[PDB]
Amino acid sequence: SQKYLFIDRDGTLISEPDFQVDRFDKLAFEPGVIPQLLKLQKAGYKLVMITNQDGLGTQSFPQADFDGPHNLMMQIFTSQGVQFDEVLICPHLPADECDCRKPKVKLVERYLMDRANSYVIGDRATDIQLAENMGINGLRYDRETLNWPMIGEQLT
Amino acid sequence: QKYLFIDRDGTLISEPPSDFQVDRFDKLAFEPGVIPQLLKLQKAGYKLVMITNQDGLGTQSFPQADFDGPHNLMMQIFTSQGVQFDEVLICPHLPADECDCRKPKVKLVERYLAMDRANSYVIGDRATDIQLAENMGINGLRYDRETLNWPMIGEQLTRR
Ligand SMILES: [Br-]
Ligand SMILES: [Br-]
Ligand SMILES: [Br-]
Ligand SMILES: [Br-]
Ligand SMILES: [Br-]
Ligand SMILES: [Br-]
Ligand SMILES: [Br-]
Ligand SMILES: [Mg+2]
Ligand SMILES: [Mg+2]
Ligand code: NA
Ligand SMILES: [Zn+2]
Ligand SMILES: [Zn+2]
Image (tube, rainbow over all chains, first blue to last red; front, top):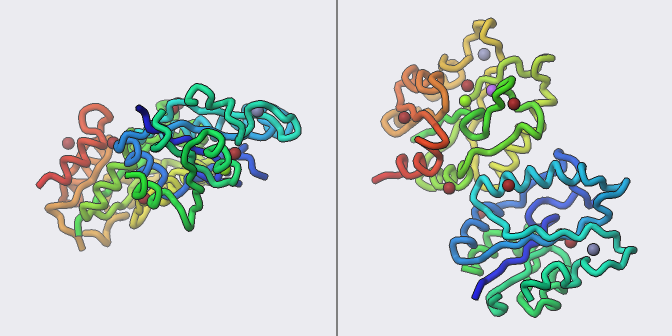
């Protein structure tokens, strides 16, 4: 059964800016993310992106402002051979108290896979809580202390 | 030292067929496999040098600020992924300028002419790139997305 990696976007795949990648000039890739995701794919992991984008589609974060950098990030990954099976987004504000905001598991219900060998990889405590809620492993990404080369090595 | 002298537009990234200049982020697109293949080439001992004509860069026809956004992002992607260019050599002149530095002229790479000529290459998509190689006394590889792409180059230049 399938090994999955459920991977956070902001602060994990790309750098976390006001916490919104709403301009092209705010886009920056995390070190080693491409070669390591390629390594992880070769080892048999399928990749799923999962992200909370607070207030996506509002005055404070229009969909168009999100789309440009996001679509470009996706181009870059895809052209280099990194493929995400799905990109799962919660667009809600915390105050909305919605059903889909990480660490709630709604976005990933369908997956609820080889649980023993699947991971959430993200840079926040809420990513680790998502792993607990899904009943799978959690890796707390840190650019300095638990980064892409380390994860690539560990999981292969 | 073995070097790869690599074109930018149409080689590392796609080249826009309207004005042939990446002056907006929506005109930036990486060529397939360029990142893993340059990493492979680096691991085999190649050093990388970027060499590019950017016609009219820094003038109203191609403002510096317009080039800088996509170019700096491109460079951030390379650097963050482990791809290091020793130098990025740019000719900003128009053809009519008759400058000393426009490819296939060798002025920009004069210091390299220094290197292992038998194992060094120019990689680019145009006749201009192949002519640069000849002018440098080294091999030229004509990049084509289908017939001589990044995976093929990665394999070819690491063949033992
Ligand atoms: Br790496
Ligand atoms: Br998040
Ligand atoms: Br894509
Ligand atoms: Br165009
Ligand atoms: Br590749
Ligand atoms: Br050129
Ligand atoms: Br050739
Ligand atoms: Mg994050
Ligand atoms: Mg070219
Ligand atoms: Na060009
Ligand atoms: Zn939500
Ligand atoms: Zn010039």
